[PDB]
Amino acid sequence: EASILTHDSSIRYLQEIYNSNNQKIVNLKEKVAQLEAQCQEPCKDTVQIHDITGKDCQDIANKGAKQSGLYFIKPLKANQQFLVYCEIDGSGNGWTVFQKRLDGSVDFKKNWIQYKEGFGHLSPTGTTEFWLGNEKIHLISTQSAIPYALRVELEDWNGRTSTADYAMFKVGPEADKYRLTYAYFAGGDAGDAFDGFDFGDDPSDKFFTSHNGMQFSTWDNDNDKFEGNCAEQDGSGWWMNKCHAGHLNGVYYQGGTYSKASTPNGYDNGIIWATWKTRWYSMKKTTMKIIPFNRLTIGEG
Amino acid sequence: EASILTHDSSIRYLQEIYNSNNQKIVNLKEKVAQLEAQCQEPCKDTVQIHDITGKDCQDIANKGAKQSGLYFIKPLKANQQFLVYCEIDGSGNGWTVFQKRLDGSVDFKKNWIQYKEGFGHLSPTGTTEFWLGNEKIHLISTQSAIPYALRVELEDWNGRTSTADYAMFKVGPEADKYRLTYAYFAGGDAGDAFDGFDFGDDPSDKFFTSHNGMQFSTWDNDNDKFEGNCAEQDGSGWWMNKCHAGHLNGVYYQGGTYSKASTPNGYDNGIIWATWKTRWYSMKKTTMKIIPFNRLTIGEG
Amino acid sequence: IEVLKRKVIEKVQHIQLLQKNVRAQLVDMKRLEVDIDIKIRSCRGSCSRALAREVDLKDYEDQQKQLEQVIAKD
Amino acid sequence: IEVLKRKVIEKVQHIQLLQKNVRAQLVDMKRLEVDIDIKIRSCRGSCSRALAREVDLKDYEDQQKQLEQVIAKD
Amino acid sequence: LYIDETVNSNIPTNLRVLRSILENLRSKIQKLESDVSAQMEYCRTPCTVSCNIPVVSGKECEEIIRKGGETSEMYLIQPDSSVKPYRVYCDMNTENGGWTVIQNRQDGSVDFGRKWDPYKQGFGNVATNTDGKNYCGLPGEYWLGNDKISQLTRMGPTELLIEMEDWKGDKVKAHYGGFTVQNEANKYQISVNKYRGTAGNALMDGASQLMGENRTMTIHNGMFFSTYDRDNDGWLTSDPRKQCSKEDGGGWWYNRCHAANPNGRYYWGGQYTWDMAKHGTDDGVVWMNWKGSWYSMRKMSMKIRPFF
Amino acid sequence: LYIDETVNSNIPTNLRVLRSILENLRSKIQKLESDVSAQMEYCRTPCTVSCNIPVVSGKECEEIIRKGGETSEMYLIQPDSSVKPYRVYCDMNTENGGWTVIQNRQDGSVDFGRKWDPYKQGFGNVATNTDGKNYCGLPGEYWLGNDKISQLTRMGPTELLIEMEDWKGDKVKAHYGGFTVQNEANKYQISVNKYRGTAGNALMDGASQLMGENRTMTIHNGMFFSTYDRDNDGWLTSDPRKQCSKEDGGGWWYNRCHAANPNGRYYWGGQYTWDMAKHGTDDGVVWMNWKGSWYSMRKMSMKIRPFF
Amino acid sequence: GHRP
Amino acid sequence: GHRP
Amino acid sequence: GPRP
Amino acid sequence: GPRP
Ligand SMILES: *[C@@H]1O[C@H](CO)[C@@H](O[C@@H]2O[C@H](CO)[C@@H](O)[C@H](O)[C@H]2NC(C)=O)[C@H](O)[C@H]1NC(C)=O
Ligand SMILES: *[C@@H]1O[C@H](CO)[C@@H](O)[C@H](O)[C@H]1NC(C)=O
Ligand SMILES: [Ca+2]
Ligand SMILES: [Ca+2]
Ligand SMILES: [Ca+2]
Ligand SMILES: [Ca+2]
């Protein structure tokens, strides 16, 4: 039996793997500490906001900014700064964008407070739908008596684009609801739907579908010239009369063309501009933006 | 009876006064001829026109004219020359005046063609009321792109005067009605009433009472931003909105102060300038005049 | 008879002389009165004032018929 | 006897040492496997992707009772 | 025989009428010298007007009434870009308005017995100040010149309107739908046509109360303009006093001599006679076919308008 | 005697058991080194997101819901005019919405075993891309920093809401009507009150399954914040290894040591034991009053609101 | 105005 | 957990 | 959008 | 002035 004691050696075998295993564990814990040092940062966000600031996108463009994208602005009378999308050109013109339609992802049937404050999303590439907010449009367009211009840009389901300019554009205070006012239609291939249109269903159509001097309305705050509620019937937020001839915050129809049956009450409620297409053609893309009038927009210097 | 024949003498007595009457006739006839010679000229007219001409009053002043008064002018695009009142100072500034009020002798409730062609009278002393005519104001202010300035001069019923200046003043053609356009208010104690005024009736007052970009209106040619007829209600021809904050072609009231009951429709229709006096205070004197901007009017040189 | 019937007929001639002369001189005076009226009135458009006056050819016409009778009834 | 029952006893103490030792290394190994599963998963929020893996402490659990039977049943 | 009565009968009355009259004329004479002398003093100062200029203007009174000028008053017109603008009285109320006045008579405040050069250039007053106003809304008596008239008529088809009124207030017209006056080198020859109206067609036919040759020598149509220092009349005479402009007393389109004499002498009251007239003729503001030869109008005017 | 059987019986068997387990532990170790090395390769590239920014902004998530911001997603907030705007997840659906999320666990995608500076500045992902949208509507795992949270609670009375979910979907809540976190010089000292909820009051009363002094040393209120390189706990020891933050694995308001361990280690499947836990303690995302010490949540979140 |  |  |  |  003083042989079976061959175990002396076998036992020393086991002791060796036991000891290398322990060190291999210590080594592995070192390697785990080195993976940890690589897993500390957050995912990288592609969206970024520029640091230059000013009273509006034109003030930003005069301070040197060259790129289109996200910036903070702060008009004189404004209490807090707010984010906007600035459209900058090679000619140094800085446009502040307040409305964008491009794919139907956002729902534009919002209430009085959502039209006041703003809804939708901002993007550095300008590839998102939004409404900037009536309070903001009011603050930028009425800073110390500086004539402002509005430019509307349309696009149809064939790549074809048209524009429409308005001089001395202003949005009024919340106490005047946010009345839209402009002096004159300043040109453009899309024509002047703000002047109203004669749809022919009646001799009074042109007068009841003009937009100058109309208060803003939403389904829960009616200030239209109609006995019913234009905003609740057409499903949007807009400067309604009885009810409209231009309607960019309307319903997004895929394909352009749509008909009375597609509508929920039998009225045209799509993204329309009556001097460019029928009331039964809804646009593919839209943009509303503003700039001090002395600049471009059929402008001086 | 050859003594009664004493007639021979007394017959030769009549004969003498016959012949001496005869020769008194002939002498009086020569006196009538001298009187005829002195009664051939017409009455002397105290008014005279100066002989120096040019494109506007500043062009006339630069050619040598020193005295204020009546001259013919002829802008390049005008078809026929026309008379104007020129105000010329010691400094060489030639203002062409296009509106004058001063005593209420001329009625300003006139029609589209009268406002276009001009009415009232022109005097060498500058003591007459008149409207020069939209067509002429247009031709002078749109001359080959040369910036014009406007000066409004007001006088109250107490000896006080004030002024208001506007840069890059223009009046548009008849096709666009005779749209008023300016780039910025350039200063003056009267205040900027063309910017609009918050009268306190409603929060929309300011945006309904501004005049930059307004079209010209008359009772028979309504181009205002109002559903009614501003020109017909206030009795004038003006660049109406809804309706006004500045109104120099309004109704003339003795002593300035007037009230709603004096008015035929209950609206303020007098000669007002809301940034300077209440809407119920009508000016004693007014003057609207223009000059190339490079001159005075808060001008360079 | 000379100093008489002859002298009478020698005065009568001179009386018919004056009759025609005064006929002529009444016509001259009626014409000058008219000429002076017309000329004073045409000073109203050049001079400070025209004299206000009145003209009646009456006194002129009586003296004419008057004159004519005597001349006639001769 | 030294070269026998004594030598046996000498070796039994060494096996008993091993036994306890491997009892503690199975616990270290279970703890390292769970710690590595948690740290790899925690890279999902920073890195392009995290390794898909599956842990099951059953092979560890089979081995721990197994060893406990031997240690106990001694 | 007994006829020697008349020596202490008639003679002494004859001398009685004559002597009276003679000494009455003496007293009229000096009373006339005394009127003429008071008027000479007044003529030491002139009459004055202050005629401020309406803003509105044009080529003639018809373009002005089209441009909004609806009141009758003095205006400035520029018929042609080559001529300097000048003053005219514009009648905006008769026959639809737009009438440019060319001649006016109404009181007798201007002398019309003038030479060729004043008739060429114009004379008289176009307008006088309305009671208390800064503008001249009342017409005065005047003659627009002959060169201005000729240019107005050759710019296009022009109608002529002649209005008159008697001392009781009756009013008549003579309207000529076609009216032209040549230039000076053609002696201002007149041509008229298309007559209408109540006064009587004196210009084209002559005094309807005369017959045969006596009528046709009173036609004005086709005549030249004559003045007292320039004879272009239709009367071939050798005596220098025998000129229609010297008798008749104005400047006019005389033919041996006239049926109409606007531009004649202003007789106060209407009626006048041969023995009131300077040369024994029917001078006087006459229109034979209406009131004959011996009646002078209270008002007489000539005015024109484009026709169209 | 016969005990020398075990020489050919028992020893050989022991040697059998020991041999298989030691070789088996040796192959597991090599595979785990292969796993750590693969993941280090993957970590040469980063994850990315594109988070388009909602137009609507304000001081915190409660002002934003009152501005009309009705969907849950990432917003920009500017609690202070002196501070620069920063990103946060707004929860607009639970308990009437307007909640500003301060901490979030849901998957174990982020490491919470960090030092003092990372806990102060914040770490982790506020939001990720919703499948096929251009905005981030899903919350990621994160810790807002300690300076941001202290400032948010110091603007005014503030309420705290803690929500959790286990691995079979049951859910409970803990509400604190008052919550303040002091500044860094005061070590982020916590205060809470006015509890209500179904999860049990672990912050103010400690673990309900302990008694007396054992219970009171697990209360969190009144404590300072500790991290593994900054001991500010409630345990007064000498052994450097005796630190609640080194055992237990996160940064928290430890007290000898805890009743709740949000910030703990995320164990997959929920159950864990002492021989799975690095230091043999209850580390792991714990809420003792709900599920005891040895159960780690599937979901755990912390969020605050101005109150009013 | 005629002259025989 | 607690620490006894 | 008229409202006939 | 203004109008409502
Ligand atoms: C506090 O907790 C401990 C358990 O961790 C309780 O412990 C006595 O503690 C000793 C030391 O661990 C143990 O050996 C005994 O088994 C425990 N005895 C009893 C009777 O429990 C202690 O009781 C707790 N204190 C209170 C107040 O509950
Ligand atoms: C013309 O009139 C005279 C009177 O002057 C008259 O004698 C003569 O007969 C008249 N001639 C004609 C043709 O009538
Ligand atoms: Ca309504
Ligand atoms: Ca109107
Ligand atoms: Ca002759
Ligand atoms: Ca401690």
Image (cartoon, coloured by chain):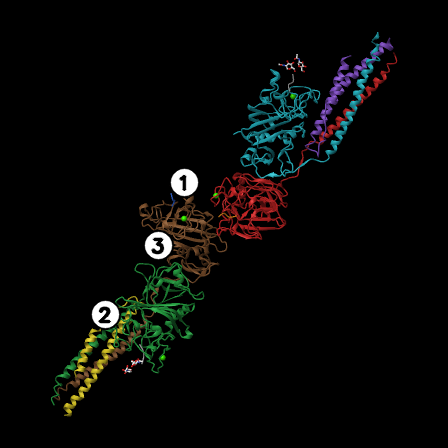
Chain colours: A brown, B red, C purple, D yellow, E cyan, F green, I blue, J orange
Mark 3 residue type: Asp
Q: Are marks 1 and 3 in contact (CB under 8 Å)?
A: no
Residue wearing tag 1? A203
Density class for disc 1 (Cα within 10 Å; few <14, some 14-19, many ≥20) is: few
The answer to which quarter of the image holds residue C71 is top right
Picture quadrant of ligand 6: bottom left
Cα–Cα gap, marks 3 and 2: 43 Å
Residue E21: where, in percent of width, then height?
78, 20
Cα–Cα gap, marks 2 and 1: 76 Å
Q: Nearer the viewer, mark 3 or mark 2?
A: 3
N-terminal of the pair, mark 1 or mark 3, is: 3
Residues B275 and A278: in front is B275
Question: Circle 2 sits in a helix, a strand or a loop, which is it?
Answer: loop
Same chain for labels 2 and 1? Say yes or no: no
One can see residue D8 in this view: yes
Q: Please, which chain is the residue tagged with disc 2 on?
A: D
Question: Circle 3 sits in a helix, a strand or a loop, which is it?
Answer: loop
Q: From this view, report whether residue E12 is shown above or below residue E172.
A: above
Residue wearing tag 3? A107
Cα–Cα gap, marks 1 and 3: 34 Å
Residue B244: where, in percent of width, then height?
52, 47
The residue shown at (77%, 16%) is C20
Residue wearing tag 2? D54
Q: Are marks 2 and 1 in contact (CB under 8 Å)?
A: no
Q: Quadrant of the N terminus of chain B?
A: top right
